Length: 222
Length: 220
Ligand SMILES: [Co+2]
Ligand SMILES: [Co+2]
Ligand SMILES: [Co+2]
Ligand SMILES: [Co+2]
Image (cartoon, rainbow over the protein chains, first blue to last red):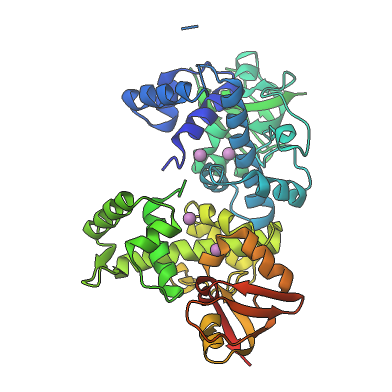
């Protein structure tokens, strides 16, 4: 189902870090729909293998493995959108499985094919291109970018859509709404002022984002 | 490691059928590098789930359910192999091992896109037919037999999945020119269980009986 439980535990910790959220067992359980028992046993198996280690934090090995999974995921997402032509809202679900079966060998081919891509189709930067040995490393979080929930709470304003985090992409219906209204990387949006739904307004229309969703969407305020 | 054990056992039995090899637990143990105890326990569980049946010969037979599931995995495998060669440009001898993992995670949604992208492909890059394209909704002889029957000039048509597991061998075959669509000269051999001498365009090579068996050709 998860295809690789360890890699999905590694990448969910890395996802929470990109979302600026503290990695906690309770959140890993909520994200991967796992029981408290299952998480505690999986975390136990991973710290033994020297992947993770206050009160969760990745090791140098676990961080590299987490990044290599994310790299495969986002290279897979580009391949699926740009070449294969799978629907924008269905691509993440596919990449969630593909990320666990891709060699570094096929990645190097995909990097050349896609022309040294830096971001996923959802605007998220592709990490570990230095460890693959075909590009520069990236910061998990760009300090220039602001979160739609922060922009809203701070009084709103017009902003450029930059990143939609992996957590948002688990809902295809939501990804369909964002595509229609025009909340997509490179498009400008109007974030209305405001635990209360954030009103976002595109060129065509708008939609209401839950705090957790709004937090995951990162924008450049004009 | 195998990604999906059940799917690999189903496709390994389907492989042995395509290769004209009697499907025994010993064959699965060799192909999937499993221990005897592991293979026996897996086959037992798969029979309970109605995927295969064990004959009195001790030989394994896929149910209509098991075949249907085996066909879907193989379809994904060969659609992945075409994508990996024709589009992505992964090396000829490295693509099978890649497809061997991809085959377990590819949706039908993607398969339908790959069918359109690759222009309705009928065979893998290794010449093996792509099965279950209908279900998705969109005189060949073995080199070992041709050799034993006096050899001759033959068009290479298919290289079985068994041969593709050895990248070094696939490199030799690529060099000498034993590849789907290229003519070869199969030299006659007297003895059974003796290596088959094949002459390609760019030189000659020595195939073991099991390898020669796995390659299918159209005699000219
Ligand atoms: Co994604
Ligand atoms: Co995944
Ligand atoms: Co193959
Ligand atoms: Co496989």
